[PDB]
Image (cartoon, helix red, strand yellow):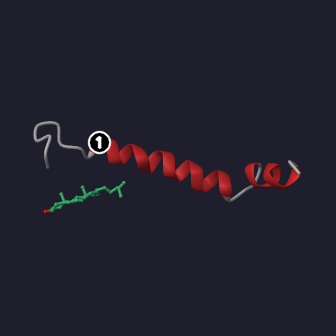
Amino acid sequence: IRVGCHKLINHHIFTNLILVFIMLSSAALAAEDPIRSHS
Ligand SMILES: CC(C)CCC[C@@H](C)[C@H]1CC[C@H]2[C@@H]3CC=C4C[C@@H](O)CC[C@]4(C)[C@H]3CC[C@]12C
């Protein structure tokens, strides 16, 4: 059934966790070293 997966997508805590992961995955991009490739 597609109803079970639909409820999780349109949830209150699931959409917050995926949103805080997006703004935290960006910080992983800013911390990279551009000079030393092998670090
Ligand atoms: C968890 C991620 C996505 C957000 C936090 C990222 C920052 C705060 C973390 C990610 C990897 C970490 C680095 C991993 C390895 C080292 C080498 C060590 O000799 C000095 C600290 C240093 C340089 C860490 C500093 C903190 C660091 C840059």
Determine whether the residue tagged by mark 1 lies in a helix, strand or loop.
Answer: helix
Q: For the residue carrying disc 1, how many other residues have a C-alpha within 10 Å: few (<14), some (14-19), or many (20+)?
A: few
Q: Is residue 8 left or right of residue 2?
A: left
Q: Residue at left 81%, top 48%?
A: 6
Q: Which quadrant of the figure shows ligand 1?
A: bottom left
Mark 1 residue CB less than 8 A from any atom of ligand 1: no
Q: Is residue 20 left or right of residue 5?
A: left
Residue type marked 1: Ala
What is the quadrant of residue 35 in the picture? top left
To which residue does mark 1 refer? 30
Q: Is residue 36 above or below residue 16?
A: above
**Between 30 and 5, the one nearer to me in the picture:** 5
Where residue 28 sits in the image (x, y, percent)?
34, 48
Give the tally of numbered discs.
1
Where residue 24 sits in the image (x, y, percent)?
43, 50
Where residue 19 sits in the image (x, y, percent)?
57, 48
Q: Residue at left 58%, top 56%?
A: 17
Q: Residue at left 49%, top 45%?
A: 22
